[PDB]
Image (cartoon, rainbow, N blue to C red; front, side):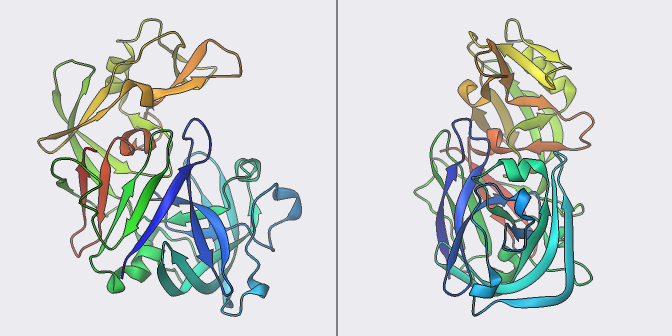
Length: 330
C-alpha cells in the first residue's frame, strides 16, 4: 500500500503545515500537524474542555462506529516550545492520503495549552518520530507510520514541504519526479527517539564551506532552524544591522535587508536554503524589525533542522530495520 496527502501552510509565514486526516466511520476529517519530532497522534475532541476550543474541528468518538475506548489509557505531552496537551485514548480507523490503519491509537485531548487553543487551523498532531517517545500510559502506543509500515510497498515516508505553498507527505514510496539530482542518505540514531543525524557542515551565502559535524534532528513540527551559537553568529554577522535581542527572544534584522542563503551538508552533498526562507517578517505588526529563521539552539539542548531547513529539500524518512534519512534538492 501507499498514501499521498497534500500539506498546506497554516499562514503566510509557513509557521506550520496541516494535512487532512480521516478518522473514524463515517470519516471525520481533521487537519493535523505532522510532526517528525514527536510520537503521539492527538486531536481536539468532544472531550476537550470547551473554553480551550476556539475554531478547531473536533473528533467525536461517539459518532464513529469503529471507535473503542482504550480502557485505562491516558496521555500527557509537553513540547519543546512549552506547549502541552493531555487526555484519554481511543482506537479507531485512521487514513492519510488513501492509506488506512485500523486500530490506531487516537489520543483525545481533555486539556490543551493556550498556544493550541489560539491556533484555530490546527486540529491536532500526528507524530512521526519513533514510537519509543509515545506518551500513552500504561501501555505505550505505536505511531501511524509504525502501524502502517508492514503494509507499505517500502518502509518509508517522505516530506516535501513548500515555501509559501502546498507540498506533499507520501507514505510507502519515493516519488522520483519530486526532486532533482540524487538523494543522499545519512545515518540515523534512534537513541533519543528522534530522526537524529549529523550534518557535515555549513556555508553562509557564497562563503566557503566549513566542514564540521552538527548533530541534530529532522523535525517537521518545528518552524525554524536551530543551530549552535557559533554557526548562527557567523550567519547573522553577514546581515547589516542584525543582532540578538533578549527582549524579542532571538536574532532580529532590519526588514530592509536582503538575507544571504544558508547551506548545510548532507554527507558530500549540499542543501541550499534561500535567504527568503529565513525571513519571518516583522516582530510585531508594522515593525521594521524582522525575525530571523535561523536561531541559536543554546539552551534547547539539541540542534533542530525544522521547516526552514526541511522545506529546502525532498526528505526521505527511511524506517527500514536500520533507519536512515535522505535529502535531495528540488
